[PDB]
Amino acid sequence: MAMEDFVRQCFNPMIVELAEKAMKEYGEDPKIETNKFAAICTHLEVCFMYSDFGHRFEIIEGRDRIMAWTVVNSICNTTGVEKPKFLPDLYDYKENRFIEIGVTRREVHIYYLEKANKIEKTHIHIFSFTGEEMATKADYTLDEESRARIKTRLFTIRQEMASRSLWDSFRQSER
Ligand SMILES: Cc1cc(=O)c(O)cn1-c1ccc(-c2nnn[nH]2)cc1
Ligand SMILES: [Mn+2]
Ligand SMILES: [Mn+2]
Image (cartoon, rainbow, N blue to C red; front, side):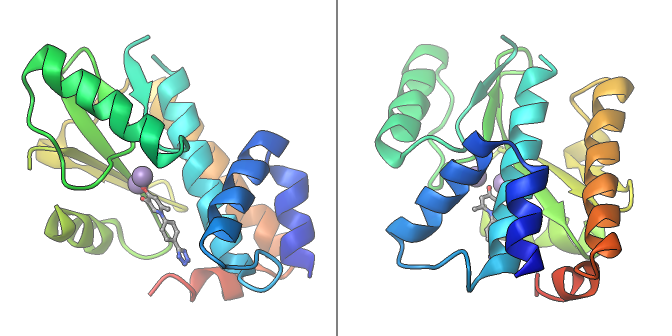
């Protein structure tokens, strides 16, 4: 599969490993569920980039569940903030809130609504592969440069996928 090859070449090995381990532990094969594999890599990378454009942020996504819940409980005890029912992706020590991050092949408002419906006062920030984004109360958290880097990376993934005739498949597999 070109899609499998694509993932191993455009994402750094730690992201690939993490994505692979996550999938294999739940009995899903990345050579079969290849569009899922790429989406998980893409989401992971956006979480890591967002964290790097701050020690403003604590990365929760990409840890195993013990560590993620350990990080969340330690943040809840020492700030007073409410425990989420689901692990979010980051904590913002400046604004003193958890963040859920979304990356969508469809319209940002549509995906924003789905996330909001699955959730507390977790802040939501959605990115598209088109440079559109949406966030709770239109508070975009990061400065424009950091946001522009994420969008560029996301647009570039799309374009790479399009080069290899993978983007049409990838687009229609979110649902
Ligand atoms: C795994 C995951 C964590 C998140 O925080 C988040 O926003 C999205 N995902 C995620 C990413 C992609 C999928 C998916 N499943 N099938 N195709 N894509 C399911 C979940
Ligand atoms: Mn997550
Ligand atoms: Mn997320």
